Amino acid sequence: KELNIVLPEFEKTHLEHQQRIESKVCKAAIATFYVNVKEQFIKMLKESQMLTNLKRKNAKMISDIE
Amino acid sequence: AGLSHYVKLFSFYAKMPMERKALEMVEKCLDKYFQHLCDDLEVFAAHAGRKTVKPEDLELLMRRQGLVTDQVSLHVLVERHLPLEYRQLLIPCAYSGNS
Amino acid sequence: SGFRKELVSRLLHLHFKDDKTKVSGDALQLMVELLKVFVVEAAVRGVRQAQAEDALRVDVDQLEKVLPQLLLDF
Amino acid sequence: TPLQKRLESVRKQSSFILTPPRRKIPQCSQLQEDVDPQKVAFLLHKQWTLYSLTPLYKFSYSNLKEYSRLLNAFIVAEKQKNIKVIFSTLLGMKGTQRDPEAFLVQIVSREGKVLWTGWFCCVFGDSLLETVSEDFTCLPLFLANGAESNTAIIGTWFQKTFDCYFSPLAINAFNLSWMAAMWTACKMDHYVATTEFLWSVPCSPQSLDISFAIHPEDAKALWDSVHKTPGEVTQEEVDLFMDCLYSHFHRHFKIHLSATRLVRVSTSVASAHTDGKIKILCHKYLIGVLAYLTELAIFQIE
Amino acid sequence: KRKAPRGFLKRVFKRKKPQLRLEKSGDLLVHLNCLLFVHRLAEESRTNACASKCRVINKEHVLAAAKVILKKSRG
Amino acid sequence: LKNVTVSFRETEENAVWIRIAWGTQYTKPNQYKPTYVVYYSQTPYAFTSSSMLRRNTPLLGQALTIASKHHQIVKMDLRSRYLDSLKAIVFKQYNQ
Amino acid sequence: MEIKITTVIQHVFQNLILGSKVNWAEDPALKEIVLQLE
Amino acid sequence: SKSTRDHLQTMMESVIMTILSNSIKEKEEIQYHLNFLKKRLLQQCETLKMEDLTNVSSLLNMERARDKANEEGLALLQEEIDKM
Amino acid sequence: QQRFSYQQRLKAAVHYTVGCLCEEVALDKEMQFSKQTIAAISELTFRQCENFAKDLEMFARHAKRTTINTEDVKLLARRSNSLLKYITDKSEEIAQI
Amino acid sequence: KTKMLNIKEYKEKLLSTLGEFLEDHFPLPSSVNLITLHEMLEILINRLPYVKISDSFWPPYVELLLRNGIALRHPEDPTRIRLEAFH
DNA sequence: TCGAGAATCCCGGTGCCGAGGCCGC
DNA sequence: GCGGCCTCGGCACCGGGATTCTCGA
């Protein structure tokens, strides 16, 4: 949900930084930072998947009890 | 003696009852404390090139122990723990005759 | 390789609280050695407590449990 | 008038002239003015150990900070022999406008772990106000709940600074049966707890206790059997309610409950013990339960 | 306890190491060092006691205290 | 209850003193609040420490009545703190 | 707000003609200024 | 979640460490990109656990593997019990 | 600004040379240093290099001296027995240079 | 008013002696004369301060008014001084 | 009609102050 | 075998488990 909007803002932030960019190597550094931000967003998505897996365990903590 | 002085002072420094079997091991802790110190004063006084151990020879050592800082100098540390007639010898007072 | 000369001049001189203290190359390369063995010692202590826990990875928490004796020792 | 009025009051009380206090059924006491909802709601379901508190000499509801400091510095000194003391006027625990405003004494320990939460209240206690001079702010009731050790320390501080004395208020089984009857006579709904009467037989070698716990609606219908005059409950009506309990217990177990003594009468209104750890205040009738409790504290003071 | 032994610290400094010239009140500095070392011992041993929630300091807490503080107090 | 630490102790009065530390498959066996079961060896009566009366109580009775070759487990509804008196009552062993 | 300065400067005469090389009472000026009346 | 995204940007700063190790020839230019990353902080944190997240999530994933084993065992032994 | 461009550029240099050291010490015990692991050990090298700089300056001040010589770092090597023995031989190797 | 003038003259007695007898003490090697250092402490405590010198110089002097109880070190940050609050 | 969530009756499992024991004078 | 010392333990007040009973698949 909000993760898609955050990724869109991060891409817009990277694009605005490239609009004010000065060099080609700076563009490569910005691309590397964008890949790092994608990894951070993947960590956030892994946290969301951990919440989903905890919901499954809660169902799995009741199915086993049942 | 003095180790018995420190274990008794440990009682009023730990604020909490301990065991005598703890005290003879803290005695070995003080013995090794000197076994590190008196040769740490040895090596620090040798580092200054002086045969004797001046007060600044130990101020550096206590800087090593992290107890002297830019906030807590040597002399302030004397305020908090040593009695008055003892810090009268260490930190220079003033009479136009500073000790 | 190592932690080179123009970098050991610069890194140490950043924490220098005055401008007039220099560290000579004879002592500079030994400073390279002492912080190189800072990495070596911190790493060996971490991997040693790692075999003590039997890991193939050095995680975040291993380093945090090694500081209380790393900074104390080194 | 300043003392002799109290002497005449003592004469009237000791005379014991036809006591049976036909009491009004505790009326739903809509929470007067402020009565901090958080504070009062925190003060309800707490087991107050009652005490009888003589009037406080030279007390003022302005110098709460000074007494707070003077008592905080005394409690932690009794530890020399971490704690905060918050005197807090309750602003609404009073029966009539002329009653002294009830104020708290809380041993707050870091966070708000209220260890002790004392409570002095004087509600519908105008049998003491009109007999004591202006200098005394009389609060007959004192409410502990904290450990007995801290109560026996704040009580000493209060004796030392205010010349007030704490007799541990012990509700006799007669007054206990009275309150057990006027609380099943109330007009409440959604009864929180069963109407339990913890009896305790007087056997010398053994100490058998009985919990004659009635269904709260079933005791209300049993009370209506013995309730004839509305508005006020009589001593005979209370005794007939208690005797219907007796004739439903001796009927069943052939042991005369009337030969035993009440020790605790739990009710949906308010639990009430004998030995002092008395007043749990389940419902918000506490200005009426406290009215009875203060009227009982006058009996001990006067 | 409100004391600091002049004789004992000097006798220890001479017994352990025979070759020094500790100054007029340098042994007083040694006493301050040991006072603060035992301060650290008392406080971190209180921490050790709360670590196992033991209401009395015992051997198993002092031995853990030593390897931290005694090593820390090394110059 | 796949994670339980059941520990027996055949006492000298010929009464196996079962102790059960409970815990579901999701959790480790909890030794904080165990459920001691004093099963007299060949007796139809099997005392039980009324710890929490959870969903294991119908499994405590079930395992008890299927281990010992019985079929129906019934709580007698005798609940006393003095096991040395419950032993007397359920066996009629007090006046003899 | 002035006696509260006169109970401060006073008590730094009970602590300055004490800690220094005072020769406090063997002097006729300080003897009336030390032993300062409350 | 302020401290959590501070750990986010310390991972950002570790990646910054990496690029500056690889780049080191953009000193004013990665001064600029550290500037845009600091206003990225000012854009996300101003507007608005993880080690516990990853570690506890792996632990709980092993827990759900153990739970699937529990259901395999319990459910199958229930199939055998009600097969009986 | 200048404080940031100073310490972040040396944080970068420390990470770069310490990552070279990470590849040089990861081959001994067949280990891998994760990104946050390198990021940590680099900043402990930084933070305790602050400690070494704090120590070494007053070490020269202790001998009434302005320059830092080998005995000062020997006192820095005074701290621990294992690296006393390690730094003794590495110091005679220093003197070989 | 008579008590005002009496206390004022007592103050100009104590402070006149603080000028006179403190020439028995008397400054010596900015440092800051103990008259001036003391009065800078005293001005700060008069309105409250706990800093009052921010570690005034000539360390023999600052620790002078600390051992006799004249001034007090800040219990947490011991580079700032307070004048013992004789109030 | 039924399945998960919340509240709350029933009794713990805990907190904490008197009683009994115990070691100098 | 007592003097100020200390340690179990009945009583009791506060914290989750299963039954009520309301709502969603």
Image (spheres, coloured by chain):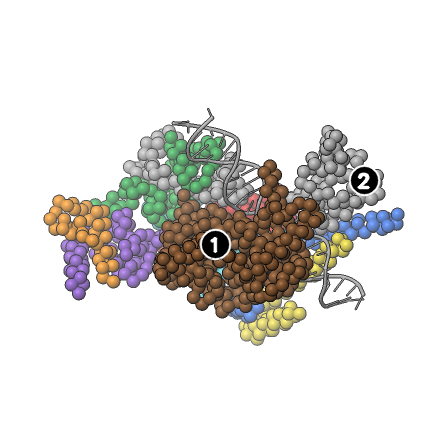
Chain colours: A yellow, B green, C red, D brown, G orange, H blue, I cyan, J purple
Nearest the viewer among C47 and D250 is: D250
Counting from the top left corner in percent of width and height, residue H34 is at: 52, 66
Locate the N terminus of chain A and report the quarter of the image it occupies.
Answer: bottom right
Which residue is at 82% across, 44% downward?
F72
Where, by quadrant of the figure, is residue C18 drawn? bottom left
Which residue is at 41% across, 44% downward?
D80
Given the image, on which type of amino acid does mark 2 rest?
Ala
Q: Up-down: is A23 above or below J39?
A: below
Which SS class for mark 2? Answer: helix
Chain ID of residue with mark 1? D
Q: Does residue E33 appear in the picture of this structure?
A: yes
Q: CA distance from mark 2 to mark 1?
A: 72 Å
Where, by quadrant of the figure, is residue E13 drawn? top left
Image-based side of E16 in relation to C58, left or right: left
Image-based side of C28 in relation to A64, left or right: left
Locate the C terminus of chain A and report the quarter of the image it occupies.
Answer: bottom right
Q: Which residue is labeled 1 in the image? A: D16
Q: Up-down: is I76 above or below D137?
A: above
Q: Up-down: is F4 above or below D189?
A: above
Q: Does residue A47 appear in the picture of this structure?
A: no
